[PDB]
Image (tube, rainbow, N blue to C red):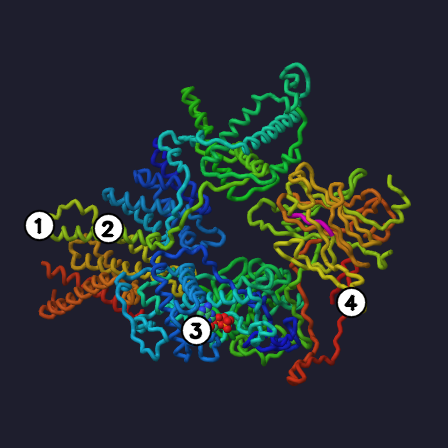
Amino acid sequence: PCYEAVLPKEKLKVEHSREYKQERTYTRDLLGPTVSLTQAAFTPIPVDTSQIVLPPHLERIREKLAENIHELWVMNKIELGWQYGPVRDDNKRQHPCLVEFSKLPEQERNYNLQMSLETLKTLLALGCHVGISDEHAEDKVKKMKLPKNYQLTSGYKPAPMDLSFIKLTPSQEAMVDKLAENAHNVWARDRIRQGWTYGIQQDVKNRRNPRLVPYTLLDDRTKKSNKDSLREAVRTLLGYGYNLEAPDQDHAARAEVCSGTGERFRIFRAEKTYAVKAGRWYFEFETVTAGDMRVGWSRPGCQPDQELGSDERAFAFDGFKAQRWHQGNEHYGRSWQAGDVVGCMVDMNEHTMMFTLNGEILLDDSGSELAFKDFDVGDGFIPVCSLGVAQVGRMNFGKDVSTLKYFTICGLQEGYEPFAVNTNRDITMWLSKRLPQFLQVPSNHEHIEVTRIDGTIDSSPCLKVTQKSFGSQNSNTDIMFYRLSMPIECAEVFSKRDDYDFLMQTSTYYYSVRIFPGQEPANVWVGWITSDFHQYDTGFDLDRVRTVTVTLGDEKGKVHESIKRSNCYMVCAGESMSPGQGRNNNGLEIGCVVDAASGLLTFIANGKELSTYYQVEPSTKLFPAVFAQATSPNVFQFELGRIKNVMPLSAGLFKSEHKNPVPQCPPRLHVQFLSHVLWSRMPNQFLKVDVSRISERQGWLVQCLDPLQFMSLHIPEENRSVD
Amino acid sequence: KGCSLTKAQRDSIEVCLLSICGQLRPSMMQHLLRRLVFDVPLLNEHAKMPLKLLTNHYERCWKYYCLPGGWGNFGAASEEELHLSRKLFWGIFDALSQKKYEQELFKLALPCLSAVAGALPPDYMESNYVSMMEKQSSMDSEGNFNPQPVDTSNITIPEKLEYFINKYAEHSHDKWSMDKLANGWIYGEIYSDSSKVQPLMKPYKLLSEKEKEIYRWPIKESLKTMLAWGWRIERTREGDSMALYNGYSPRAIDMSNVTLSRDLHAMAEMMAENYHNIWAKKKKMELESKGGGNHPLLVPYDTLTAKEKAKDREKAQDILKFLQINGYAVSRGFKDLELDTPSIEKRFAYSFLQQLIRYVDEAHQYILEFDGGSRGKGEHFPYEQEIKFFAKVVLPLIDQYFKNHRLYFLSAASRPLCSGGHASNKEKEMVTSLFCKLGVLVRHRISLFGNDATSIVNCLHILGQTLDARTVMKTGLESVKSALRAFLDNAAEDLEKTMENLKQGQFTKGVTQIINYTTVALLPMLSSLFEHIGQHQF
Ligand SMILES: Nc1ncnc2c1ncn2[C@@H]1O[C@H](COP(=O)(O)OP(=O)(O)OP(=O)(O)O)[C@@H](O)[C@H]1O
C-alpha cells in the first residue's frame, strides 16, 4: 500500500500537482524554482577504506584496544542486565558470547576486531590523523576496578582509566559523530546487499526493514545506541593516549545547485498593456522568505531568461548584497529579513525611482535618496520581480488601498497612487515559462545564423545553419535543438529516370542532412521528432529519450499487439559512420525516408541502409529535426532533394504540391530552434477544488463542483494550442 | 633603458608609458612585468621609472589581486602573476635592505614596495610548481636577445612515430602537390623552371627517398623537443582503423576550421617561442658570420608583432591537429606530486611576518648596542643606515600593510568577509608578540629617534587599536603571553613612576627624556589601548 511510503515524521497530504491555486491575488504566494529533491532516495555511501594502510603503532595498539573495548561493551550490556548462557537465544537472558574473546565465537571476535580496524582506518580516511602524545601514556597501565558480580563471567576487568579525565573538543566530536554515521551507512550497505529495504515495521514475512532511514532522520533509540558505542570507542582511544589531531576544517559553499533543471530564477510581471507612461505610482512586495530576490520596474521588452538589472530593460533592487541593478551592480540600501515589505515608487514625469523597506526610505551610498537618478520614458514601465531558488514572495498592486500597510506612513502623503488605483477587474499577471518551445530563429540572434540556399537545376534547395560567434570568447558551447516548421502527417489507417506511375501513387518522402566538414558528427543527431518534444538538457543521448510501450492483450492475457510510443525518432551520425575518420574527405550525408502509408522510419547514410528503424502509430505528425553540438563555424545543412523512387518532402508538407515531383522550399518552411525566452499568462480564475480527510474509514475526499472554461486557439501547422 | 636620451626625452617617455600602462587592462602588462621583476632589483638610476609604474599598477589593480574574484569584468589572478609579484616584492625588499640609504630613492621606493605588499594577498600560498626555460637569459641586458636552443638530441622516437611521420610525409607531399597545382606546374619529361614542369610526377610508391628527410628531420627535431619537456604520447584505435582501411593530384582535409583547446593553444604558442628562438639562434649566428647588417626581426618573440608570428603559428596549429588526427594523445610534461597547503608557512603573510621578526630582533640588538654606545658622546655607528631603513620603510610599510589588511588579521574565518580572510590563531598571537616587542623596542627612546618617533607613535597606536587580544589570551604560546605581560607590566610601573615624578614636581637627562616620552606618547598609547579593550570587550 501507498500509505506506508510516507517519510516517518512527515505527514501525508493531498495537494495540488501544480504550484498555484485559486486565492486572492495579494495573498498569492509566488514561488521560485524549487530545490532538487535528491533526498527522497536514501542511498548509503560509505567511504572506501581498502586504500587506507594502518600505521604500525595502530596495528600494535588495536589488538588490545579491541579486546578492551569488547570487554567494555559486554560491561555496557551487563549494565542493561545481559547474562551469559549456553543458548544463543537473547530473550532467555543467556548468550555464549559474553565470555572472554577466546571462549566466545572466534568469528564474531574477528568481526569485532575488523570493525575496530574499520573504525580506525575510517578515522584515517576522514583525515583524522592520530599522534601519540607520549609513549609513557601506554607504558603506564591505569585500570578501574570491577567487582565480580557487576563483572562478566571472565575475570577480566574491562574498566579502563577513569574516563571523566578526558574531554573531546567539539570539532573532533563532530567528525566522530559523522564517523558513526558512516558506520550505520555500512550497516545499511549490508542490509541492501541482503535484500532489505525501508518499511514501517519488522516483517520477516515481507522481508522489508523499518529502520533503514538517513541519520538526520534516524530513530532515537538506535541513535543513542550508536551514541554509546561512539562514546565508548572514542573515550577508550583517548584513554590510551593515542591523541588524534583534527584535519583542517574549511568552509564550503554550494549555494543551491540543486534545482529543477537549469532554471535559477522565475520572473513575475504584469501585462504589457498596463504600462505607465506618466504620473506617479506605488506598489508593494512582501518577502515571505529572505533570499536572492529582486523587485522593481521593467520595460515591456524584458527577457524572461536574463536576470533583472543585467540589461537596460529592468530596474531592480537586491536584498542580501544590498545592490541596485541596472546595466550593472551598484551598492544601495540594506538587506531584508523575512516578512519585510520593500514596495517601490516611481515618478514618471521627472524620471526618478525610490525604494523603501518596512516604511523607512532606503538611501544611496551617498545621502541621495534617489535610487536611479534620471532615465528616458521609453515605451513605459511595468512592475516586475525575480524569485530565486526556494523563494516565496507576494506582490500587492494596491487594488484595495487598505491592504497597503506602509503606504499610509510613506507614499500616501507624498501623493503616490497605488498601481491598481482605479480598476474594476483584477490585473493579469505574466510569468516566465518553464517548458521551452520551438520558435523561429531571430535574425538578431548572434549565436545561430540560417542561410536559405536556392535550388538550381543541378542542386536541391538547401537550408544551412551557421554560428557567427564561433571561436570568440564568452561563447558558451551547448547543444542546440533545430526542427522544421511543417510536419509530415502519417496515414490515418495503415494498409495491411524513376517510374512515373510508382512515384505518383507512392506516399514515401525524403529529406537529407549534410554535416559540414570540421563539425565532428558524434555531436550531430538526425531524425524526426513530434510536437510533444519539450526536453532541454545540456547533455543529450539517445538512451534517455522518453518512451512508453502500450501492450493491449486479449482476455486470457496474451499480448496480441504491442506499440512503441516516443516523441523522438533520431539517429547519431557518429555511429552511422562505418569508417573512422573516413568522413573528413567529404561531409557525411544522412538521409531519412518516411512511409506515411506504413509508418516506417528508415535511414540511409552514404548509400547504405542503416540497421536502426522505427515504427510509428497511424496519424502521427513528425517534424524533421536535427540536434547538434557546434565544433566548427559550419554545423550542418538541410537538403530537400529526392532519392530514386521517393517523393520530395515538399509534396508531403504542402497539399497544393502533393503531386509535384520537383522539390520545393516555399517561404513558409523555416528552421525553428528550442528556446526559453517566452512568457506565460497566469489564469485570472482557477478551478475551485476542496480536499479534506473525511475519516480513516472514508479517506481523503476531493470535490470540484463549479465549471470553468477557456477558448483555446489552435495553430494547425505546429499542432499547438494556446488560450 | 636606452642611454643616449636627454632628460626631456626621458621624461616624455616616462609620462607616456605611465599614462598608457595606467589606462591599460590589468592582464596586458604581465608580459612587461616579467621583465620588470628582473630589471627592478638592480635598483639603479634607471629603475626609478619602473618603480613609479609598479606603484601605479598595484594601486590601480590591488582589488583584482586581493579579492579572489577581483573585478567581475577584469577576471581574477592566474597565480603566475602572484608568483612573479611575490618575487618582485621580496627582491625589492631585500635589495633595498642591503643597499645604503639615499633619501630620495627611499622615499620613492616606499610607496611602491608598500603597494605591492597591499596588493599581494596575505594568505598567499607559495606555488610549489616552477616554470620551464625561464628566458631571463634570452632577455639579456647586452644584445637584448639570447635565443638559447633547448637541447633535444637525447631522445629518440618509436615505431608509432615512425608510421606517424610516414603518414605525415605522404600528407606533406600532398600539400607539395596541391601547391604545385595552385602554382601551375604541369607534367612533362624535361626539366624547366619557366615551363612549369617538375621532374616529380612519378607517384609516392616510387617517390624519391631524400624528399621526406627534409620533412622528417625538422619534424623529428620538433617531436623530440616536445618529448623533451615531459610528454608521454600514446596511440588510440584510430590509427589501427587507418591501417585497416588502407606526383599526383591530392585532396586536403580542411583543417583550420577545427578549433583547439585553450591549454594546447598555449602549448603550441610556447613550443612556438622555443622553435622561433632556435630559428633566431641560427639567424643570429649568420649575423655574426656576416659581421654587419643587423636583422630588424632579431627582437624577442614577446616583442614580435602577430602578422610575422603567424609564420610559425600555422605550423604549430596544423602539426598538433594532425597529431590527434592520426590519433595520438597529449600529455603535460609534469603533474604535481603534492600540494603543501597544511603549512601555515606557505602563506605569504607568514614568511613576511617572520622576516619582520628577524629584522625587528636585529633592530633590538642594534638599539641595545646603541644604548651601550649612547654613554659615548658620538653615536657614530655603522647601523644608522639600518635604523633609517627600518624606521623609514619597514615600520611605515608595517603601517601600510596593516591599514590595507585590517579585515584579514581581524577575521578568523568567523563570519565577517564570507569570502574568507582567515588569520590563523598562532599567526595572530605571533603578530601580537611582534606588537609588544616593537613596543619594548620603542619605549623611552624618543630622543635618539631623529623626529621619526612621531611616525613610530602613529604606527604604535594604530597597532594598539588593531589587535586580536581576545584570541591571544584564549589561545597562544604562553612564552609569547609572558613577553606581552612583561611589556604591559613594565608600562605599568612606568605609569606609576610618572605619577610620582609628576606629583613631586608639577612641572617637567634620562628622567626628563622618559617623562617626555610618557607625556607625548603613552597618553595616546593608553587611550588607544583602553578604547580598543572597551570596544572589543577584551
Ligand atoms: N558481529 C557481532 N559480534 C558480536 N555481537 C554481535 C554481533 N552482531 C550482533 N551482535 C549482538 O547482537 C546485538 C544486535 O546487533 P545488530 O545491530 O546486528 O542486530 P540486528 O537485529 O541484526 O539489527 P541491525 O543490524 O539492523 O541493527 C548487538 O547489540 C550485539 O549484542
Q: CA distance from mark 2 to mark 3?
A: 72 Å
Q: Main secondary structure of the magenta part?
A: strand
> What's drawn in magenta, residue-wise?
A523-527
Mark 2 — residue? B359
Residue nearest the viewer, comparing B212 with B192: B212
Mark 4 — residue? A557
Residue nearest the viewer, comparing A154 with A293: A154
On whether residue A232 falls in the magenta region, the answer is no
On whether residue A526 falls in the magenta region, the answer is yes
Mark 3 — residue? A96
Tags 3 and 1 touching, CB below 8 Å: no
Describe the element under mark 1 as helix, strand or loop: loop
Mark 1 — residue? B376
Question: Badge 1 local density, few (<14 within 10 Å), some, or many (20+)?
Answer: few
Tags 2 and 1 touching, CB below 8 Å: no
Describe the element under mark 2 as helix, strand or loop: helix
Residue type marked 1:
Gly
Residue type marked 4:
Gly
Q: Which mark is residue B501?
A: none
Q: Position of residue A518 (x, y in %)?
A: 64, 41
Q: Position of residue B331 (x, y in %)?
A: 50, 41
Question: Badge 4 local density, few (<14 within 10 Å), some, or many (20+)?
Answer: few
Horizontal side, residue B267 vs residue A138: left or right: right
Q: Position of residue A477 (x, y in %)?
A: 59, 50
The verdict on a common chain for dots 4 and 2 is: no
Q: Is residue A35 visible?
A: no
Judged by depth in the image, the label closer to the viewer, 3 or 1, is: 3
Q: CA distance from mark 4 to mark 2?
A: 93 Å
Q: CA distance from mark 2 to mark 1?
A: 25 Å
